[PDB]
Length: 222
Length: 217
Length: 132
Image 1 (cartoon, rainbow over the protein chains, first blue to last red):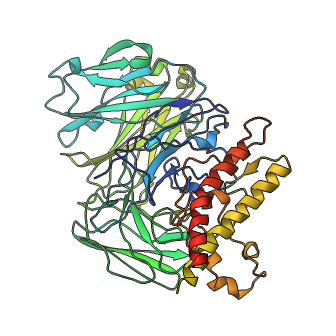
Image 2 (tube, chains in turn blue, purple, red):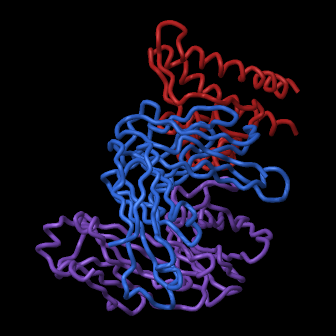
Image 3 (cartoon, each protein chain N blue to C red):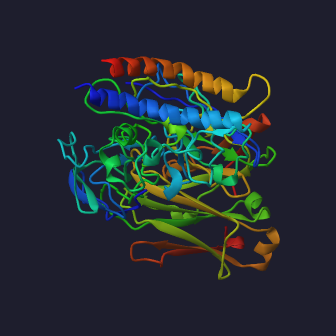
């Protein structure tokens, strides 16, 4: 089936200007076309949907009207605010969509894009406040415990984190950030540890903070 | 365009279960309809079709029905993917959005219920110099018992210094879990003796609460 | 009989002549044009001679072949028209939402030329279904 795939899933400055993209796979423009949907943060708020009625056809409420002057191609189909004052309300996830049809012939193709984010933040780069986090004795239950590594208040995304010479990443999971109005991010890695695995190794967390080009490592102890 | 409201829905009893989700329309077009599904951390997908001339319906476990100012989705074999859903249409025959979708209502797919295990975790000397502290909640399967952390320090509730999120059901262990963290200065950990998390639910508990002192960790 | 197809092609050519009338006014008045959803609308039956609330519009070929356009919400701007489907003129693509008025290579004259060229195959079909 047909495919959609976005790019430019990064950053802009408030009151500045921005331009996203599609790259629609083998798409030829037709009766059915493309359109741009604004997924709001977490909750699907009401006035959100169905920006750009057809290809290049600007349309919304007055709350963005005139900003969204999309360009053209057979594949780039580009939503765009090129001179048009990107607001804090315009930080969201912007999706390509295509006007699919059923009935097994052409245009029965999965029809939504991979969802390009838009960060807005006037932060500099900032190094993470890293902290590995030992278990309490109280947690030692069901034959199990868990450990954390907090990675607090940093910018920009993304980061690579691992444990025990980088060999420990299965039996480990990570919580993504919560994006505060201050325009920073965070993680929490957690290790699932059986009680039979405590004491059997020295435990260490590895942080590769890509924006500061530097590796930092810390051992598990209070 | 037409405003919408979607209700009700709750957890399944099992796999293979039956659930029926309705909606109300503030204004009229007929039965011009489709349902969109939002799996978490994915691109949305499409379900139901056909208009006021109610020609033949949908393959597999999906179905729906409409009259007056209401329309409804019935799923007859409710699967572990099936975890958020919405309504739409714009006026010609198919695709787009009613400028708003019908704003959806949670869905989840069951294995045995639990209440959480809850632990405070000891801050290191590096964490304590930095006035940081941390907590975990663990719960086998998704019921869920959807929850809130309430960080409290010598009976004062904490905000402007706080973080929370839920990780998905573990691939082997089926654990739902919820980390959280707090921060103040070292001088606040000198002024204040005890730091605590109250834990609260949609289920029948605002009891469950853990607390610690700086000297015992 | 062919009078229904003449009425259909007349609905296209009436709307294209309304667009040309707005363009000729903009050229005369030294004005740029806005063609998007904030601009001029093409649903109003008075563009086609029918009175305000006159139920003749409900069956009219002009309202029929304009409400049944794939961009129609109930409203229809010049751009929703100039980007829509279906039409016996075919349709354009890549059209920008505003054109300014300027002294050399004037954008509204280039736009008027663009509309005029695709109007000529419609005039051929109108000459045909008027002379048949």
